[PDB]
Image (spheres, rainbow, N blue to C red):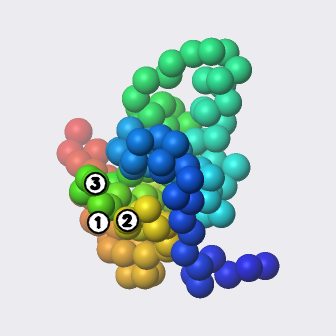
Amino acid sequence: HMDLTSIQWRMPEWVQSMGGLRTENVLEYFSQSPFYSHKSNNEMLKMQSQFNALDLGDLNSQLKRLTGIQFVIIHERPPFLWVIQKQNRLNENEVKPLTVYFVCNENIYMAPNAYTLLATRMLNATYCFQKALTKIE
């Protein structure tokens, strides 16, 4: 297979067509890239929405109800960067960070592994805390 840690992707013809990148549409941009995965809860939602002609509103709330591969925005600095995280959602309370990507100046590429490491360390500490609170009652 082609190694995605060694490429950058950029599709200027889409950006112009949409009037520039915005938090509103950055994830859609990401969807046309080889980093996207059609196995994702993201994709499943895109199609229920189109097929049923339905507005499903806040994505993040829709993702909480599902399990599997997910893509979420975890950092916003319009109009230059957004940071996206691929994660495997285990349930409504747990998520496993898989990889993170940068969308910098319309360029998409995987961030160094350390960012994923930081993410999981953040989540682990959070989850350890929450499991610790369930016991007091």
Left or right of 131? Residue 55 is right
Identify which amino acid the numbered label 3 is placed on: Pro
Dot 2 lies on which element?
loop
What residue sits 35% from the left and 58% below the top? Answer: 82
In the picture of the structure, the residue carrying the numbered disc 3 is 79
Instruction: Reply above or below: 121 against 23.
Output: below
Q: State which mark lies toward you, 1 or 2.
A: 2
Residue 15 location (% of width, % of height)? 48, 50
Q: Nearer the viewer, residue 92 or 118?
A: 118
**N-terminal label among 1 and 3:** 3
Q: Is residue 91 visible?
A: no
| Discs 1, 3 touching: Cβ within 8 Å | no
| Discs 3, 2 touching: Cβ within 8 Å | no
Disc 1/disc 3 C-alpha distance (Å): 26 Å
Direction top: furthest residue: 53
Near mark 3 (Cα within 10 A), the count class, few <14, some 14-19 or many ≥20, is few
Instruction: Reply above or below: 59 against 14.
Output: above
In the picture of the structure, the residue carrying the numbered disc 2 is 105
Q: State which mark lies toward you, 1 or 3.
A: 3
Identify the disc placed on residue 122: 1
Residue 56 location (% of width, % of height)? 50, 22
Q: Nearer the viewer, residue 44 or 30?
A: 30
Residue 21 location (% of width, % of height)? 39, 49
Identify which amino acid the numbered label 2 is placed on: Asn
Identify which amino acid the numbered label 1 is placed on: Met
Dot 1 lies on which element?
helix
Residue 52 location (% of width, % of height)? 67, 15
Q: Is the C terminus in the top left, top right, bottom left or bottom right quadrant?
A: top left
**N-terminal label among 3 and 2:** 3
